[PDB]
Image (cartoon, rainbow over the protein chains, first blue to last red):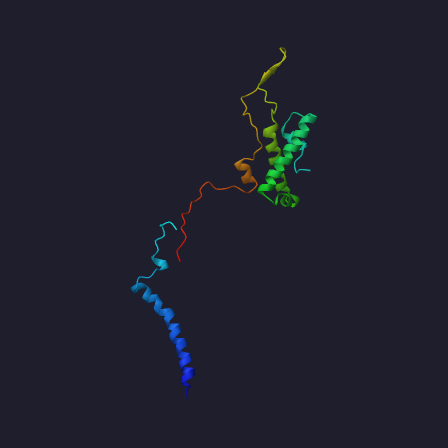
Length: 44
Length: 124
């Protein structure tokens, strides 16, 4: 029924869209820089 | 011309002025009006149609000049040996100014409790 090439396109787009969620948990396990971790009293 | 007049200043200052004191009063009135306008841009508009607000601003201009033209020569005492006077110890004033209560009459009093707010830019 469905075309494998249109299905490959449509779910490479879904795979790429998911990576923007996963980075929000990677940043805590790898201890990347986060805006919320920066203590406010420290000079710029 | 100004809203108040040398006739208004002379209504409070019971001594009738000489021509030197008239030109002084005309410039001090212009300074008092210009001082009120810089605090209240609407002044001439309010005074065009509110007849009691006219009486506020005219009597306050006349007072603001009166307290500066009263005894402007700076004499304490004077005599010719047949007549003499001396005055109460008046403040030797040198500027025109409008009182905190006169700004409250004009409706623009300011409060004496204010706040300093600490601030730091939030990160990103």
